[PDB]
Amino acid sequence: DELLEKAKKVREAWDVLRNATTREKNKAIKKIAEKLDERRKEILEANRIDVEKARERGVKESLVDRLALNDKRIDEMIKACETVIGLKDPVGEVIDSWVREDGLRIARVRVPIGPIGIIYESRPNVTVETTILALKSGNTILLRGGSDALNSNKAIVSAIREALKETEIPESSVEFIENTDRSLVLEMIRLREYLSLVIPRGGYGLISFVRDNATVPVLETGVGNCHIFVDESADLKKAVPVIINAKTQRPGTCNAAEKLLVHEKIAKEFLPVIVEELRKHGVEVRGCEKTREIVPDVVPATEDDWPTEYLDLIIAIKVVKNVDEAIEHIKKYSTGHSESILTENYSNAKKFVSEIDAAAVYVNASTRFTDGGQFGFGAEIGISTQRFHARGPVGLRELTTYKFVVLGEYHVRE
């Protein structure tokens, strides 16, 4: 039973890693960078097999590209190591601490969450990215990637463990499931005696499955049906690039704007402009009946459009009466990722920011910013969209919990 033996191994190794100094964990991560550099040949030969196998099966090249490695991409993995080494270790940070009226000292102190299961598909960089975030934060890791990237991931994991072997961090801090079979995923997300957290990455099918069936705590990096509302007093000239940025900079990633809500008092003036500009960038524009009264060639929006995240150069536009209707629309259709208001009105900005509950809520800013690098985290595993433990970018601090440390002088409870 590969899964059980490897889950036992990461749990045992955690006993050592959780109390390693940052110096030792940084040394391990530096060695990871060094072994990746040294094992380029092996990693690329393994990856050549994965790539030729995907091409044989007629996987389309945009997906092969997700799987493909070369020197530059190994360099990105190396740079990720260097970024993580430079980040502050959250382990041991005091959240707060005080002295009670009787002299008892109380503190809340951050500690590692425990072994993390990562269930992911085909991007081999994910192997390094998650590992180094886990190790830095004092967590072991159990990796299960896609059958497409299996050779690549073996070679990378082999390089990682070679590095670990030259430190005091046990090699079994990083274990990797070679059995691709997906029945294993169902077992893995129920292993509460070994894993403290699982984080699915990849398609929504896989994320839904893991989140629906897990008994181990999950951080769900959910769907991003993201709205931008253009209010009456928005600076319409500056609004245009924000909307374009949000939609077209990276349409395939989930903080892309999918929906545009537009105040009725500027709709006649603004819709012809924004629709023209969206079309210059290859965007297919769908619209409500009021949108279509104004710009008669837009594709008629259907009821299914409003909840749908396109992840493509497609957008649906609705005219709303005011910020109150904008809020009602977003509450009905948001998936709690990113939401933005473009306005010059203090009260409307304030109401929007207070009433819209999503991982990130913006005034006069692109939804593209919802990202750990942009938010000053350095590196992330992904964007959590749940209202539990962590929301937004999941970086080093989000991979910790805490405990109370209490220092007395033989204190007894009254």
Image (cartoon, helix red, strand yellow):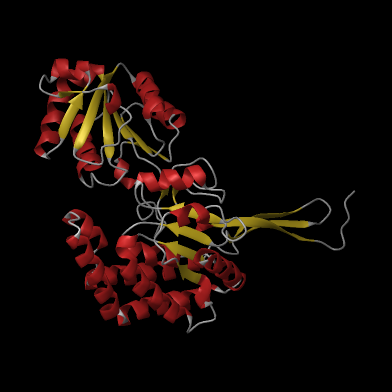
Residue drawn where x is 23% and y is 26% of the image: 317
Most foreground residue, 35 or 190: 190
**The residue positioned farthest toward the bottom in the image shown:** 166
Residue drawn where x is 15% and y is 36% of the image: 283
Q: What percent of the width, then of the height, locates residue 147?
A: 34, 61
Using residue 176 as the reference point, say whether residue 170 is left or right of it.
right
Residue 78, placed above or below residue 187? below
Image quarter for residue 160? Answer: bottom left
Residue drawn where x is 51% and y is 60% of the image: 116
Using residue 279 as the reference point, say whether residue 264 is left or right of it.
right
Residue 346, placed above or below residue 387? above
Using residue 98 as the reference point, say whether residue 60 is left or right of it.
left
Image quarter for residue 240? Answer: top left
- How many numbered callouts? 0
Residue 345, placed above or below residue 197? above
Q: What percent of the width, then of the height, locates residue 152?
A: 31, 70
Q: What percent of the width, then of the height, locates residue 72?
A: 23, 70
Using residue 407 as the reference point, say whether residue 294 is left or right of it.
left
Q: What percent of the width, then of the height, locates residue 285?
A: 17, 30
From where the camera sits, is residue 25 visible? yes
From where the camera sits, is residue 18 visible? no
